[PDB]
């Protein structure tokens, strides 16, 4: 059963701005997604400090980057706290609305698209490089869900019956035809070294077969 939802007007506007604005410094999407992973990992780590059983769904706290040339996807996987259905339907939309308003105001005051992450909407930088984004997520005491959107004003959510992930978030970027540079080992290594050198969790860049 697949449910389709409308983005709030302000979030659709943000996505169209990201998709339509001429802006060459697209590589920052990776910094933003890795930063999101670090935050999700910090959250589960903090919870585990007072309740060790929070890690029953997996003790390892890390990030995997997985390029796949055949599927034309770059996947960012973390074992962080994950997301509830309420996150995907209501919570992150409430945060995105106020964050978008502030991001828009900053852009008018001379800020640039790379500063998106400072407004709690860095996730949407994925649309700088991806035609479709699929997110698989699992939070303790909630079911595994797949969220998906190719923008255009709507997203879907379904309960995911594919491979179980234990706990965390997996962002699958279906890359635009002209953005396949972010599948090259040398390029990903460069971007990670440049923007994500002090992340407090292992980042493993998988090699392609
Ligand atoms: N403003 C954001 N929106 C998302 C976000 C998202 N938004 C569309 C929901 O209908 C879908 C998704 F699959 C992952 C996301 N992942 C993130 C990153 C994030 C940030 C804070 C969080 C979070 C995830 O989960 C709990 O608190 N965001 N941030």
Image (spheres, rainbow, N blue to C red):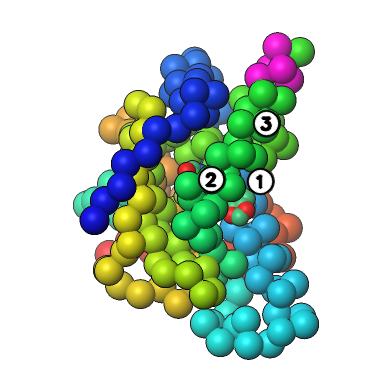
- Which residue shows up at 72% across the image and 17% down it? 105
Q: Where does residue 100 sit, x and y in percent of width and height?
A: 63, 28
Q: Where does residue 203 sit, x and y in percent of width and height?
A: 57, 64
Mark positioned earlier in the residue sequence (1 or 3): 3
Q: Where does residue 205 sit, x and y in percent of width and height?
A: 48, 62
Q: Name the residue under label 2.
A: 90
Label 1: how many Cα within 10 Å (few below 14, some 14–19, many 20+):
some
Q: Is residue 88 above or below residue 160?
A: above
Q: Mark 1 points at which residue?
A: 195
Q: How far apart are marks 2 and 3 (CA)?
A: 13 Å
Q: In which quarter of the image is the C terminus?
A: bottom left
Q: In this view, does 13 lie above or below 58?
A: above
Q: In which quarter of the image is the N terminus?
A: bottom left
Nearer the observer, 52 or 69? 52
Label 2: how many Cα within 10 Å (few below 14, some 14–19, many 20+):
few
Residue 7 in the magenta stretch? The answer is: no
Residue 121 position by quadrant: top right
Q: Where does residue 136 sit, x and y in percent of width and height?
A: 40, 59
Mark positioned earlier in the residue sequence (2 or 3): 2
The prevailing secondary structure element of the residues shown in magenta is helix
Q: Mark 3 points at which residue?
A: 98
- Which residue shows up at 51% across the image and 60% down it? 84
Whether the residue carrying mark 2 lies under 8 Å from ligand 1 is answered with: no
- Which residue shows up at 51% across the image and 75% down it? 141
Q: Distance between the residues labelled 1 and 3?
A: 26 Å
- 197 sits to left or right of 157: right
Mark positioned earlier in the residue sequence (1 or 2): 2
Residues at discs 2 and 3 in contact (Cβ within 8 Å): no
Residues at discs 1 and 3 in contact (Cβ within 8 Å): no
């Amino acid at each position: 059963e697949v449910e389709t939802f409308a983005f709030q007007a302000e979030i659709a506007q943000l996505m169209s701005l990201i998709i339509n604005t001429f802006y060459s410094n697209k590589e920052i999407f990776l910094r933003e997604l890795i930063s999101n992973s670090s935050d999700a990992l910090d959250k589960i780590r903090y919870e585990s400090l007072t309740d060790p059983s929070k890690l029953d769904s997996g003790k390892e706290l890390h990030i995997n980057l997985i390029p796949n040339k055949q599927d034309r996807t770059l996947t960012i996987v973390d074992t962080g706290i994950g997301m509830t259905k309420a996150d995907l339907i209501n919570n992150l939309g409430t945060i995105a609305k106020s964050g978008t308003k502030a991001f828009m105001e900053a852009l008018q005051a001379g800020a640039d698209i790379s500063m998106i992450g400072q407004f709690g909407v860095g996730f949407y930088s994925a649309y700088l490089v991806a035609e479709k984004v699929t997110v698989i997520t699992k939070h303790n005491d909630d079911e595994q869900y797949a969220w998906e959107s190719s923008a255009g004003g709507s997203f879907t959510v379904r309960t995911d019956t594919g491979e179980p992930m234990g706990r965390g978030t997996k962002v699958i970027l279906h890359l635009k035809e002209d953005q396949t540079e972010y599948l090259e080992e040398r390029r990903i290594k460069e971007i990670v070294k440049k923007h994500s050198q002090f992340i407090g969790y292992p980042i493993t860049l998988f090699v392609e077969k």
